[PDB]
Amino acid sequence: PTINQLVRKGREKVRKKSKVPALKGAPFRRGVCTVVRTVTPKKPNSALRKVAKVRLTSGYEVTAYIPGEGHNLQEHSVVLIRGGRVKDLPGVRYHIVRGVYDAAGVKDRKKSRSKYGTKKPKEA
Amino acid sequence: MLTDPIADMLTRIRNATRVYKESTDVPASRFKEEILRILAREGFIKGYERVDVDGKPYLRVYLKYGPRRQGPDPRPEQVIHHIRRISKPGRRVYVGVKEIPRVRRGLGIAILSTSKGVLTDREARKLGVGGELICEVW
RNA sequence: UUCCCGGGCCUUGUACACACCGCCCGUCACGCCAUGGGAGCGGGCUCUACCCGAAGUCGCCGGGAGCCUACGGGCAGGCGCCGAGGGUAGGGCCCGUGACUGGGGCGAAGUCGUAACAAGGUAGCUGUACCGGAAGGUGCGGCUGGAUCACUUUCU
RNA sequence: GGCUAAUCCCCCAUGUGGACCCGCCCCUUGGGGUGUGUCCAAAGGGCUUUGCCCGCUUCCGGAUGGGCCCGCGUCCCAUCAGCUAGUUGGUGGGGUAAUGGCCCACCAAGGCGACGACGGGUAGCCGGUCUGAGAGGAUGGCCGGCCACAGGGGCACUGAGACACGGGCCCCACUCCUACGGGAGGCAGCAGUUAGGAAUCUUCCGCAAUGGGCGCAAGCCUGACGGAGCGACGCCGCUUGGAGGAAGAAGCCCUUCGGGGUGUAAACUCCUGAACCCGGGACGAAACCCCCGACGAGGGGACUGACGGUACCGGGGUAAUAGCGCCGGCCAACUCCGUGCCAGCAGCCGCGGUAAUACGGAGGGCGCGAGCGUUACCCGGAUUCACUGGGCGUAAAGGGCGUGUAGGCGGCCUGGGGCGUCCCAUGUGAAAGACCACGGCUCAACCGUGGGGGAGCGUGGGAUACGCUCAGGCUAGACGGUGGGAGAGGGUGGUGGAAUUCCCGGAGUAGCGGUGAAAUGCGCAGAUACCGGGAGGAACGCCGAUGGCGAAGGCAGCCACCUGGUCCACCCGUGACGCUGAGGCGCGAAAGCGUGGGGAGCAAACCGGAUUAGAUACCCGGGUAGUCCACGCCCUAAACGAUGCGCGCUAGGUCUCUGGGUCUCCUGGGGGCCGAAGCUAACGCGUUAAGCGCGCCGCCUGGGGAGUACGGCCGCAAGGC
Ligand SMILES: NC[C@@H]1O[C@H](O[C@H]2[C@@H](O)[C@H](O[C@@H]3[C@@H](O)[C@H](N)C[C@H](N)[C@H]3O[C@H]3O[C@H](CO)[C@@H](O)[C@H](O)[C@H]3N)O[C@@H]2CO)[C@H](N)[C@@H](O)[C@@H]1O
Ligand SMILES: [K+]
Ligand SMILES: [K+]
Ligand SMILES: [K+]
Ligand SMILES: [K+]
Ligand SMILES: [K+]
Ligand SMILES: [K+]
Ligand SMILES: [K+]
Ligand SMILES: [K+]
Ligand SMILES: [K+]
Ligand SMILES: [K+]
Ligand SMILES: [K+]
Ligand SMILES: [K+]
Ligand SMILES: [K+]
Ligand SMILES: [K+]
Ligand SMILES: [K+]
Ligand SMILES: [K+]
Ligand SMILES: [K+]
Ligand SMILES: [K+]
Ligand SMILES: [K+]
Ligand SMILES: [K+]
Ligand SMILES: [K+]
Ligand SMILES: [K+]
Ligand SMILES: [K+]
Ligand SMILES: [K+]
Ligand SMILES: [K+]
Ligand SMILES: [K+]
Ligand SMILES: [K+]
Ligand SMILES: [K+]
Ligand SMILES: [K+]
Ligand SMILES: [K+]
Ligand SMILES: [K+]
Ligand SMILES: [K+]
Ligand SMILES: [K+]
Ligand SMILES: [K+]
Ligand SMILES: [K+]
Ligand SMILES: [K+]
Ligand SMILES: [K+]
Ligand SMILES: [K+]
Ligand SMILES: [Mg+2]
Ligand SMILES: [Mg+2]
Ligand SMILES: [Mg+2]
Ligand SMILES: [Mg+2]
Ligand SMILES: [Mg+2]
Ligand SMILES: [Mg+2]
Ligand SMILES: [Mg+2]
Ligand SMILES: [Mg+2]
Ligand SMILES: [Mg+2]
Ligand SMILES: [Mg+2]
Ligand SMILES: [Mg+2]
Ligand SMILES: [Mg+2]
Ligand SMILES: [Mg+2]
Ligand SMILES: [Mg+2]
Ligand SMILES: [Mg+2]
Ligand SMILES: [Mg+2]
Ligand SMILES: [Mg+2]
Ligand SMILES: [Mg+2]
Ligand SMILES: [Mg+2]
Ligand SMILES: [Mg+2]
Ligand SMILES: [Mg+2]
Ligand SMILES: [Mg+2]
Ligand SMILES: [Mg+2]
Ligand SMILES: [Mg+2]
Ligand SMILES: [Mg+2]
Ligand SMILES: [Mg+2]
Ligand SMILES: [Mg+2]
Ligand SMILES: [Mg+2]
Ligand SMILES: [Mg+2]
Ligand SMILES: [Mg+2]
Ligand SMILES: [Mg+2]
Ligand SMILES: [Mg+2]
Ligand SMILES: [Mg+2]
Ligand SMILES: [Mg+2]
Ligand SMILES: [Mg+2]
Ligand SMILES: [Mg+2]
Ligand SMILES: [Mg+2]
Ligand SMILES: [Mg+2]
Ligand SMILES: [Mg+2]
Ligand SMILES: [Mg+2]
Ligand SMILES: [Mg+2]
Ligand SMILES: [Mg+2]
Ligand SMILES: [Mg+2]
Ligand SMILES: [Mg+2]
Ligand SMILES: [Mg+2]
Ligand SMILES: [Mg+2]
Ligand SMILES: [Mg+2]
Ligand SMILES: [Mg+2]
Ligand SMILES: [Mg+2]
Ligand SMILES: [Mg+2]
Ligand SMILES: [Mg+2]
Ligand SMILES: [Mg+2]
Ligand SMILES: [Mg+2]
Ligand SMILES: [Mg+2]
Ligand SMILES: [Mg+2]
Ligand SMILES: [Mg+2]
Ligand SMILES: [Mg+2]
Ligand SMILES: [Mg+2]
Ligand SMILES: [Mg+2]
Ligand SMILES: [Mg+2]
Ligand SMILES: [Mg+2]
Ligand SMILES: [Mg+2]
Ligand SMILES: [Mg+2]
Ligand SMILES: [Mg+2]
Ligand SMILES: [Mg+2]
Ligand SMILES: [Mg+2]
Ligand SMILES: [Mg+2]
Ligand SMILES: [Mg+2]
Ligand SMILES: [Mg+2]
Ligand SMILES: [Mg+2]
Ligand SMILES: [Mg+2]
Ligand SMILES: [Mg+2]
Ligand SMILES: [Mg+2]
Ligand SMILES: [Mg+2]
Ligand SMILES: [Mg+2]
Ligand SMILES: [Mg+2]
Ligand SMILES: [Mg+2]
Ligand SMILES: [Mg+2]
Ligand SMILES: [Mg+2]
Ligand SMILES: [Mg+2]
Ligand SMILES: [Mg+2]
Ligand SMILES: [Mg+2]
Ligand SMILES: [Mg+2]
Ligand SMILES: [Mg+2]
Ligand SMILES: [Mg+2]
Ligand SMILES: [Mg+2]
Ligand SMILES: [Mg+2]
Ligand SMILES: [Mg+2]
Ligand SMILES: [Mg+2]
Ligand SMILES: [Mg+2]
Ligand SMILES: [Mg+2]
Ligand SMILES: [Mg+2]
Ligand SMILES: [Mg+2]
Ligand SMILES: [Mg+2]
Ligand SMILES: [Mg+2]
Ligand SMILES: [Mg+2]
Ligand SMILES: [Mg+2]
Ligand SMILES: [Mg+2]
Ligand SMILES: [Mg+2]
Ligand SMILES: [Mg+2]
Ligand SMILES: [Mg+2]
Ligand SMILES: [Mg+2]
Ligand SMILES: [Mg+2]
Ligand SMILES: [Mg+2]
Ligand SMILES: [Mg+2]
Ligand SMILES: [Mg+2]
Ligand SMILES: [Mg+2]
Ligand SMILES: [Mg+2]
Ligand SMILES: [Mg+2]
Ligand SMILES: [Mg+2]
Ligand SMILES: [Mg+2]
Ligand SMILES: [Mg+2]
Ligand SMILES: [Mg+2]
Ligand SMILES: [Mg+2]
Ligand SMILES: [Mg+2]
Ligand SMILES: [Mg+2]
Ligand SMILES: [Mg+2]
Ligand SMILES: [Mg+2]
Ligand SMILES: [Mg+2]
Ligand SMILES: [Mg+2]
């Protein structure tokens, strides 16, 4: 646009919108599991993925992926969620942190342990 | 009328040189003539001269180019590779001596207009003055 | 050599490219989700008018109604304006919930036809208008972003 | 109720002086001086006690601190456009340290707003901080400055200062006490508790140091501060060992079953020797005070350490923590087994459905290391809001067109001014931070000293090219004159012929019509085909185009009238009168709406006939709105060149419409085609630009959701923006 125009209207700054209304920007939010279903991935994939409807302290209710081999989340488990969607299950945008509160860590895990709350295998 | 006579001139020249014209006429004004002098002195044109096209004053601007060339497209290189207007009605640009630019690490020039007359970025830097940055040429 | 089947060369259109046994559209069914409208019932703000109005400064009185007095005046006390706040009537806005209700996004292999893409088999698109399970059909006008020179016939 | 001291309160005096009224002088807003009149002072205490100390009163000045005022700067939304009555100003008061509608009477009727008033949202601001090549973006924690607040609201008192966090009064909410009348309280001080949260510490030590309050001083007070404690939260430093060790143990992992890998890695050999144990043991602390001297300058002496028996120095001395992520591409690092679209991975692209370097494990490998990863958030890359630094023919993007307001922009010459612009000097730009240098802790982090910068703003001086402004001039832009021209440009009235339909007459007879084929339909009340007459509505064949006119939508028989635009010639007149144009106003195909009229043909809907698997279609026969006119609405479109308007510049060739000329040809305006240079992703564009440039407007910023919802405005409605 002409300079006169930029003088009259100027450029407009881009407002970046969140993908994680875990409110307070907060790195994590605590919640309680309502449901503890399983879901079908979209088109390219197929499997039974472990999700979990969660009622957050954030004053929110949303589905959150339950990573790892196997869990133990009933209908009243105290869980901590973090940002991180699951490209296959539209609608799931957070992950449960396996190793905090009720969601136990993964057992017999030996590689990416910290990412699955599994303490350093005892013994020598 | 023309909205910017100096840009009109800078272009008549830009155009003429792209089709290797001999000279090119531009309506006359003292200010325009003053710019040609720098243009001449720095060796971008062969010079110019007042003439009267029809009944009104113009300025034949004898252009200048390099030698014929080798391979496909023998057309000569340009003396004036680049000539661009900087200040413009609608957006005038003024600079302080400390802010005068340096066209192509010196291989080119900037023509400022100061209260000490029209000068190149050196004549200006030398006389320690700044002003309206008219254009750059290289 | 028009037709049916297979094929060759040139050209043209194409939204096709595991390449027409291609692509693809809308209704409906099933699931997940966010959301519009919304009677009523809660919560909040605000403005206008009238009314009640604490504290306090300020103003007037301070008198055979009080205390002090060197009679000048002071204090107590009283009244008044303003005044936080409250009330009533109405006006406007926001918020929660909400029976009922509208459509939308997303989700391998459910249903119906076949609208579009090749002249897509009635060229298409389009503004408008009426009509119809659905894509859509038809009228009027416009555009080219339309193929060649001049019965109908779905799907994969 | 009663007694009583003072540096408590009051009265008289003294008047250096100062305040107030009036006058005069200088000065210039209420500054300084002067005169008369009036008004206004005080406090004592201690002594090494008759000479000092501490203090008191009035005044002038300094210093520090502060009030008030002004210019400029300071986020988002115009789906917030009008706001305002103490409101805007005046006179006179009140109030204050002081100006002021700060407050109050009375008078005026003003003030503010697209340069964004008012409203809504959000938010302490700054030095700085993070990021970035920069411009810029984001940010305001620690530290330093300013502001505001001290449970919420209001108020004043005291005082140099407060409208007062640990002062007071009232209202409100809450907690506690209550013999129910009534009282008490406010950690956003330090530490701590509880709640909320993903998450943020010790109810520590000291007053030794620096700083503060009171005191003559001794000294007292100081959760300010100086320290220690907790937490890898960050930064920096450091350790888990060094040298020698096999053509290479075992175990484990691959294998071509030869062998290869972990790897000099280990065990071992020698060396040093973190931790730990002893001994010593600090700077920070010399003032205040006392003595001499004069209570000064100067000199002398004494006391004082929380940190801490810590730092550090010396002696002795053990070989003694390693983890985390990753290895399909981007991206550095590969093999076996397991699993079989499962379990699962996943930042994006994607991976897994039997031999997966992508899932899980193992071996090996890459990266980094007291850390490593993850999530969240800011800048970057992103020239992806483009000022530096982008775009709109077909990718998202030209407004449907005109007229025009504000605004932005402005041809040639001369002169004044000197606002912009530029230069010089000067002031300001705190400290910290940042940069450079030297220096102190063994280094560094950290810290000290010094130096160098700095935009912006104030002041003084100067320049005048460009911009601005004023004054004068010019004719190349624009406009006008005179004379010619072309045209489906617009409005009103009139009018012509062809055809369709209907009606009337004649003549004539069995069908016509329609389709792929049919049928519905029409016809013996005589249709179709043919001739003659009449009525009416709508549209204009040939000319006609590859043409013309218009700003667009659009405009087509012919005649007249009224009326717009435009081109050429002549250089005749004006003298920059110009371009663009947010908003405004007008115009705006078709369909559609309202009122009235008209209605031949055509034809949404609709009624039927066929077709089809069905056929709410395509084909056939009918047919209402409508299509037509008037007046008033609607305001859309593939409203298209999918290309905003204006001006200057940059080969030509060829066709054509309209004008002028010395009329093979030249020259002006318009319409096409091919093409120079150049531009373009390509296609293509190319003097009719999509080239090279300047001015101004409009518009774009991934797709779906959606031209939807909400709001506002407009409309009768449909519905438009
Ligand atoms: N999400 C698509 C949107 O809704 C419509 O599309 C919706 C339906 O028409 C469509 O339905 C399709 C159906 O068309 C097709 N013939 C068969 C198919 N099984 C259906 O599929 C649907 O349902 C199944 C479960 O039954 C889901 O697993 C699947 O993800 C979903 N797309 O699925 C869509 C919902 O996902 C519009 N036509 C489309 O243009 C629009 O973008
Ligand atoms: K034949
Ligand atoms: K739909
Ligand atoms: K009395
Ligand atoms: K295409
Ligand atoms: K008493
Ligand atoms: K006197
Ligand atoms: K003083
Ligand atoms: K002062
Ligand atoms: K001051
Ligand atoms: K006044
Ligand atoms: K820059
Ligand atoms: K900023
Ligand atoms: K800021
Ligand atoms: K800043
Ligand atoms: K003192
Ligand atoms: K001394
Ligand atoms: K030692
Ligand atoms: K060892
Ligand atoms: K296997
Ligand atoms: K496979
Ligand atoms: K692997
Ligand atoms: K793996
Ligand atoms: K970014
Ligand atoms: K458009
Ligand atoms: K419009
Ligand atoms: K001048
Ligand atoms: K910086
Ligand atoms: K200056
Ligand atoms: K034409
Ligand atoms: K109707
Ligand atoms: K009409
Ligand atoms: K109209
Ligand atoms: K002629
Ligand atoms: K090309
Ligand atoms: K083409
Ligand atoms: K609306
Ligand atoms: K209405
Ligand atoms: K409308
Ligand atoms: Mg898969
Ligand atoms: Mg993420
Ligand atoms: Mg992994
Ligand atoms: Mg064949
Ligand atoms: Mg063949
Ligand atoms: Mg052949
Ligand atoms: Mg071909
Ligand atoms: Mg072919
Ligand atoms: Mg609702
Ligand atoms: Mg009252
Ligand atoms: Mg009162
Ligand atoms: Mg009283
Ligand atoms: Mg009130
Ligand atoms: Mg169709
Ligand atoms: Mg079709
Ligand atoms: Mg079709
Ligand atoms: Mg087909
Ligand atoms: Mg058809
Ligand atoms: Mg078709
Ligand atoms: Mg087509
Ligand atoms: Mg249509
Ligand atoms: Mg129909
Ligand atoms: Mg049509
Ligand atoms: Mg088929
Ligand atoms: Mg008494
Ligand atoms: Mg006196
Ligand atoms: Mg005086
Ligand atoms: Mg006097
Ligand atoms: Mg007297
Ligand atoms: Mg006296
Ligand atoms: Mg004494
Ligand atoms: Mg006054
Ligand atoms: Mg006063
Ligand atoms: Mg006021
Ligand atoms: Mg008014
Ligand atoms: Mg705030
Ligand atoms: Mg950048
Ligand atoms: Mg930097
Ligand atoms: Mg910066
Ligand atoms: Mg601070
Ligand atoms: Mg509190
Ligand atoms: Mg005091
Ligand atoms: Mg106080
Ligand atoms: Mg205060
Ligand atoms: Mg307190
Ligand atoms: Mg908690
Ligand atoms: Mg102390
Ligand atoms: Mg002290
Ligand atoms: Mg070995
Ligand atoms: Mg070794
Ligand atoms: Mg030893
Ligand atoms: Mg002491
Ligand atoms: Mg003594
Ligand atoms: Mg002495
Ligand atoms: Mg001494
Ligand atoms: Mg690699
Ligand atoms: Mg198996
Ligand atoms: Mg499994
Ligand atoms: Mg395998
Ligand atoms: Mg590999
Ligand atoms: Mg990987
Ligand atoms: Mg950027
Ligand atoms: Mg730009
Ligand atoms: Mg772009
Ligand atoms: Mg487009
Ligand atoms: Mg246009
Ligand atoms: Mg105009
Ligand atoms: Mg104007
Ligand atoms: Mg000018
Ligand atoms: Mg101007
Ligand atoms: Mg100046
Ligand atoms: Mg300076
Ligand atoms: Mg500084
Ligand atoms: Mg050093
Ligand atoms: Mg320094
Ligand atoms: Mg400077
Ligand atoms: Mg100056
Ligand atoms: Mg001058
Ligand atoms: Mg001048
Ligand atoms: Mg003039
Ligand atoms: Mg004429
Ligand atoms: Mg006409
Ligand atoms: Mg007739
Ligand atoms: Mg008859
Ligand atoms: Mg007869
Ligand atoms: Mg019959
Ligand atoms: Mg008969
Ligand atoms: Mg009959
Ligand atoms: Mg007939
Ligand atoms: Mg007849
Ligand atoms: Mg009739
Ligand atoms: Mg035209
Ligand atoms: Mg047209
Ligand atoms: Mg005319
Ligand atoms: Mg003339
Ligand atoms: Mg003249
Ligand atoms: Mg219209
Ligand atoms: Mg119409
Ligand atoms: Mg009508
Ligand atoms: Mg009618
Ligand atoms: Mg009728
Ligand atoms: Mg018909
Ligand atoms: Mg049928
Ligand atoms: Mg029909
Ligand atoms: Mg068109
Ligand atoms: Mg040329
Ligand atoms: Mg031509
Ligand atoms: Mg031409
Ligand atoms: Mg021509
Ligand atoms: Mg044409
Ligand atoms: Mg070329
Ligand atoms: Mg190509
Ligand atoms: Mg061309
Ligand atoms: Mg041009
Ligand atoms: Mg738009
Ligand atoms: Mg979107
Ligand atoms: Mg999006
Ligand atoms: Mg969109
Ligand atoms: Mg619409
Ligand atoms: Mg209306």
Image (spheres, coloured by chain):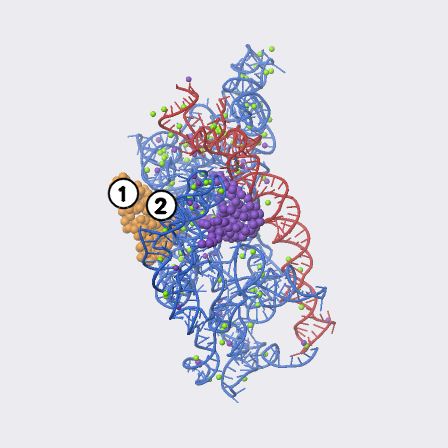
Chain colours: A purple, B orange, C red, D blue
Q: Amino acid at mark 2?
A: Asp
- Which quadrant is the N terminus of chain B positioned in? top left
Please name the residue that numbered disc 2 is placed on.
Answer: B8
Q: Residue A91, percent across and down?
A: 52, 44
Q: Residue D291, percent across and down?
A: 46, 84
* Left or right: where D674 falls relative to D125: left
Please name the residue that numbered disc 1 is placed on.
Answer: B76
Q: Amino acid at mark 1?
A: Pro
Q: Is residue D422 above or below residue D286?
A: above
Chain on which label 1 sits:
B
Q: Nearer the viewer, residue D601 or D101?
A: D601
Category of crowding for the residue at label 2, using alpha-carbon neighbours closer than 10 angstroms: few (below 14), some (14–19), many (at least 20):
some
Beta carbon at label 1 within 8 Å of ligand 150: no
Residue at mark 1 to residue at mark 2: CA–CA distance = 24 Å
* Left or right: where D506 falls relative to D281: right
Q: Residue D288, percent across and down?
A: 48, 78
Q: Nearer the viewer, residue D282 or C9?
A: D282
Q: Residue at x 30, y 41 (%)?
A: B19
Kindly state the secondary structure of the residue where label 1 is placed. Answer: loop
Q: Residue at x 30, y 46 (%)?
A: B80
Q: Nearer the viewer, residue D406 or B132?
A: B132
Q: Residue at x 33, y 50 (%)?
A: B136
Q: What is the number of callouts on the image?
A: 2
* Left or right: where B124 falls relative to A73: left
Residue D656 falls in image quadrant? top left
